Image (tube, rainbow, N blue to C red; front, side, top):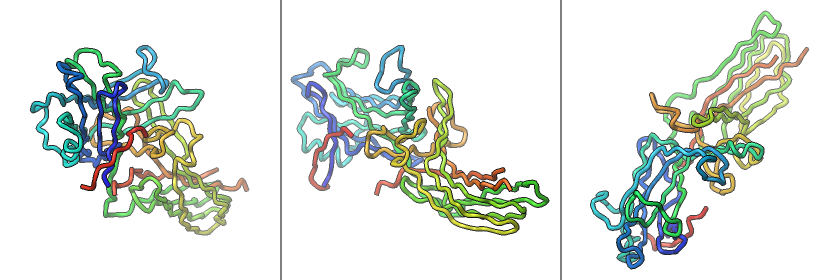
Length: 356
């Protein structure tokens, strides 16, 4: 069938319908935000119905939104007048908007938004109970409201707000293997311990295993007593309160040894996922911890020569490989990778509440 999310205003006069909650950014373009708003003329009359799409960065207690306490910076705002229509936007109606207007009445008006690709994806930094005031993130909001003009105050019984998400996808690049990272260290020795590691891919999706090929050429007389393989998330806050967070999101400690004067090679596999990091603090996520469709945040795509500050939060991931040498130092390398949201993958309509 065909699911349609909907949400009515408090007073029940205004209703918004959307074909989905998450819109995929394909780097070059973002899936269109195509919806419909069911209106009530007798109720409005002179009041027009507007629909606004806002991408904003927020900093402060997440439960609050009060001037003087919470910080907010709009990154993009688009408003359309859905009622009465007018070439506000040449409406090449989407099939869904067509079927929806059919399903609803003569009071169903379409609204459509095209989200610019250079904008940051939805992201939420969970700071921890002791630092709840350092919470922040990037959110997208669709707001339909009844008003005489975009100059006067919006009434909450007169409006409806839906928080949609923009999530990031990128296909795997058919080409060369990722470059290996290496390090050569002398451990009170004439010859070095050479550590080399590489990942099986450049791009991984949420839930996908990551295989790390570890190769050690131990030309010293010391012994590696154990190998620690981890995935680390780095999250830099770039607006309002500059800061950098780092958090392991997967870890595997292997009591594998590398004897003096020998070579060792092994593939380790780990999967980072939120499910095992719920208690972690200072972690970037792609939605609110409470929602079931939330994952670790995706890697921020930084296009060449882009203002990185207006992205709000920059998220990156590395795999770390560390050799613990026995005290008869430690040797480590880090490997960058890109974490993406998985690929998306005319039957009668079915409504469902938007509320996640």
